[PDB]
Length: 289
Ligand SMILES: CC(C)(C)c1cc(NC(=O)c2ccc(S(=O)(=O)N3CCCC3)cc2)n[nH]1
Image (cartoon, rainbow, N blue to C red; front, side, top):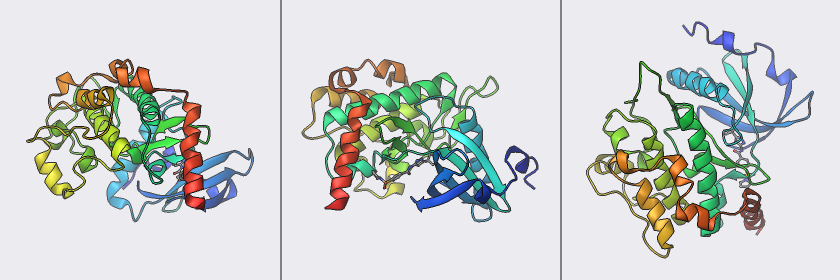
């Protein structure tokens, strides 16, 4: 019956307040838009509540989580508008695209990789201090501004720990990146995101996560039973070590995000976030050629 759902949103016509511009591409379509009064560029996600009917609980969880976050490393939520069955969510616009998009032209140098990982770790450190678990860390959900600032995105399956619930047990995530304890529905916590981060670190170096040669349902079955993936090939030892630390089957051995920010791979290859604009420049040249 969605009692209390409409109460949380503004019931004014969003078409009167925003100008829906270019389409970009969970739950619905994203557009680069503009606030008609302040002239600020925003991202507008439009969800069809009839099409996404079975995911209403997840749509609500996303807005609740986004509203409770206040950090430069987490995509900002400006507000939401309800127009019949269409819900418009006004979000921070990140014009640099995703880390997955920036991988399309070719391989990423370790300086870029470690800088992106350091920014993801700040986001995770913030979420984990707020008792939140992202639960869907992957390069697709790592977004960049046009100045190179890195922000975590997509909180539809995010989890919240409280005193009644010290651990989560929900089977959520994208199979290749999912933690063995999440797949098994064991009581898990923040360490699930540290494993996803390790998969994402391999993804940033290879353009695809480990085990991309396997069917996703086979990877779900095998992840908890087999040895964890490793970073194979022409990569530095501190990078391979960073991946090994993240990818321990026993979550007790995975370091916290705070501990990972001091890792040799991070302190040795990181540079200013502003240097990530070189990846946006490379993408522009790549698409123009
Ligand atoms: C709603 C949320 C998720 C907060 C959002 C998304 C979001 N931005 C984008 O989704 C986005 C923006 C641009 C492109 S691009 O194709 O122009 N590009 C150029 C460099 C690499 C590719 C691709 C994606 N901002 N906010």
